[PDB]
Length: 182
RNA sequence: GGGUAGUUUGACUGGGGCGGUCGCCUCCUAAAGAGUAACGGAGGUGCGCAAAGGUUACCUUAGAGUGGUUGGAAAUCACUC
Image (tube, rainbow, N blue to C red; front, side, top):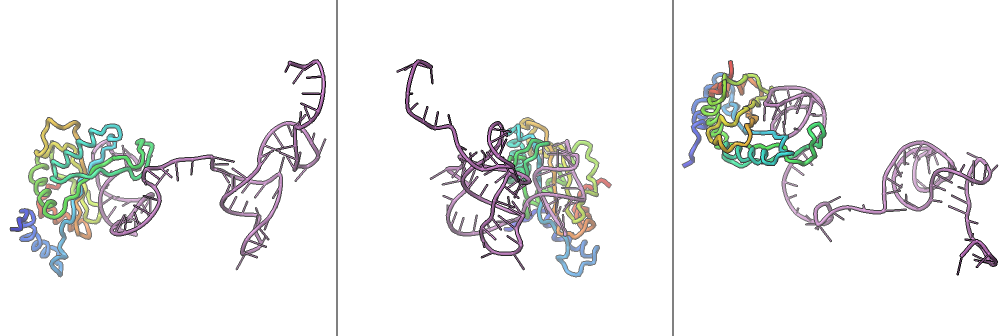
């Protein structure tokens, strides 16, 4: 059995058809879809505290399911007293089935558990179908336990879509039921 | 141990002294092969690396704009040029 995420089932069985009708696309897979979700977290203070970076990496692992990579400093800078090549950030890429499952978990479970959650700004679009927005308290995810955290942390989420514009991606996200603050 | 004796105590230098310089490497002067002077104009150097060497395989920056927890002009992430 090719086990399939419920999001993938929902997409393939409805969303393709509604978007074809709604945007008069000539051929079927002119329809937008999702290629990757990038979860990033920038801990510049890790240059003092290694525990911060280790905790962030581990908490990302529990949140998603796959291990993270610690990015390095592209350029040595003094304003943040950064030496080139130091460990500064940590990111995870989600694709395919894991991507769909994580987005389902997020939209239905973790966005609800945010303090004063009143939707998400439906305008954080880079003009090319890529939607990036932040979450300040990772504790919204029930996966991580409260006691073991060493410092409350946030993280940025970027959703990359095959769409050529923002309208297409916003329509796809709305069909997915993404709680945009509107 | 200058009581006594034998000697040394550089050169370049718009006179000599004083100052500065003395080997090697890069550019200009150098007039489109090479070479070419001045106390002409700007710099470096008396090392470093057990990989920062050898080879195989795979990747591509910086900048500007744009969307983003602290994050600000600028950190990390994504896209366009």
